[PDB]
Length: 286
Length: 285
Image 1: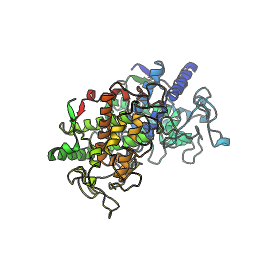
Image 2: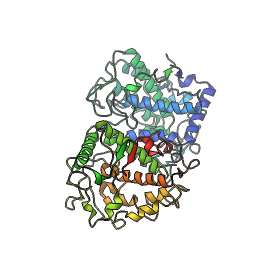
Image 3: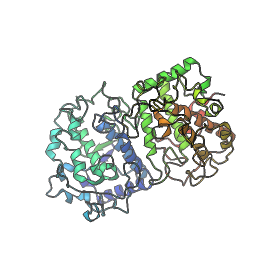
Image 4: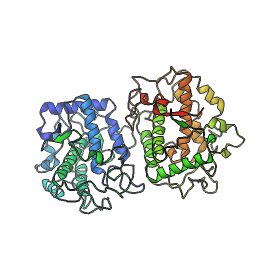
C-alpha cells in the first residue's frame, strides 16, 4: 500500500524529470534491454506449442504476467532512486480531447512526441529521440530509433473511450474457456481487445504506431510501461468491485495459464500477483 | 555435495530407465519446453546489442550460464524423482572407440541411436524417436522429429579426443579481453572451442548434427544436457587445479558478462554458481 502509482497528468515537473532520468540510467546500465528481451521471449513461448496463446498475450495470463513484469520494472527503478514509482497513462481521458496528440504526456520533457514523417516517423523530440535512445529489433540487433505514428491506421484512428473501459468493468467472469481470443464474456479478453478488434489494449498499440504498434517490439517505447500501468490499474479496479470473482482457469487450462502455474520466463505464478497491495503498491485513485 | 552426477557408462539399467522416464514426464508437463525456450531466448540477448556475444554463448558467461541451466533442470528432475540426477557424457573416452556410434549412450533404452539415412536422419529408435517425442523450432513453433547425423561434417568428423581436454586444462586464464571468440589463452574460449575450431564443444554439437548441429535448437535433443553436464565437469576439474583462478571479467566487460551481473534470462550471477558443491552436487570420482 506504500508505493503510490500516480496518473501521468498529476506528476510534478520534478516527478517527470526523476522518472525519465531513472529510465535513461536503467537503459545505460544494460538493464532496460532485459525487459524488451523478456517480452520478446514470452511471445514465442506458446501455451501449448502450436497454439496462438503464449505466456503473455492471448490467454488468461496476460494480466498477471504483465503485473509481474511491471513489478520487476518498478523494483529496478527503485534501486536507482527509491522515490520513483511507475505512473500510469490514462488513455481513456486523452481520447476525449479534440486532438489526443496534444496530451501533456507527449511533451518534450517526458515521452517526446509523434514521429517525423520526413524521417519515416522516427521520433526526434523528447528524451528518447533517435540519437539519445537505441532500440532493438525482434532478433536482438540494433534497429535505429523510435518510431511513432499517432492515429495513422484505419482500424484504430482513435484511442479507447471512458465508456469502453466502464463497459469492460461490468463483465463478471475474469475469463472463460477456451481461454483464447474467441473467449466470450471475459474481462480479460475484453481488456485485451480482440473481439471486433482492436479495442482497449490492442487499440492503444495500434493508435501509437511505430514499435508500440507491433507487440513484440513494443517495449522499445517507454510509454509501453505507462500504458501497461493503466491496464494493471483497470484490472485492479475490476478486482475491487467483483471481489467474489477470482482468476480463471484455476485448473485444466493450458500449462502456463493456470492460477498456480509458472509464468514463463519466470517462476512467478498468477496467484503470487493477485493481490496488488500485497506487492507494495497502490494506485492514486484509492 | 549430496547428489552425484554420474558418468553415463556407470549407470544401471534402472538408473538409465529412470532418467528417461523423468524427462518424458517433464516433457508432458510442459516444463521441458521452458528449458528449450530459455536457451533460445539467451541466444538473442546480445551483450552488448550489435555485438558478437550473447548471454549464454561466445562470451565469458557461457560456463556459469550453463551450470545454472543444468542446475535448474536437475532440480526439476528431483521434483519428479528425488533419486534422479543429471548424468554426464564423457565424450573424450567415447572418441577412442572403433565406432562411437555404438557407445552405450546411443542404446535403444537411453538416447536412441544415430539418424536413419532413409528418413532424413530422423531418429527412429529409443524413447525420443519420432512419434514419441515432439520438437520445437527457433521460433517456438512445432517441427516434429529429432534428427541426428554422426560425424557427417567435414569440419567435425571426430569427437574431441582426449588430449584436447588435457590441453584446455593447462590454460591459466579463465577468460581474457575482449571476452569473445577472439579471446586468447582463455580457458572459456578453448572450451567453447570456436577459436581455431570447431574444437571440443563447438565440435561435439556438430559431431551429433540434426538439431544439435544448430545451437538454438540444440536442447530439443535430450543429449544436450548430457553434453553440457560433461562440459560443466571439465570446468569443475579446472576449478580444482586452478582452484585460485576465479572468473573474468570481474568488472568492466559487457553487462551480462561480469561476475556480479545477472545472467539473462534469470537474476542469477556467475558468482552464485562458481562453487558447484555449494549448489548441492558433485561428480562421481
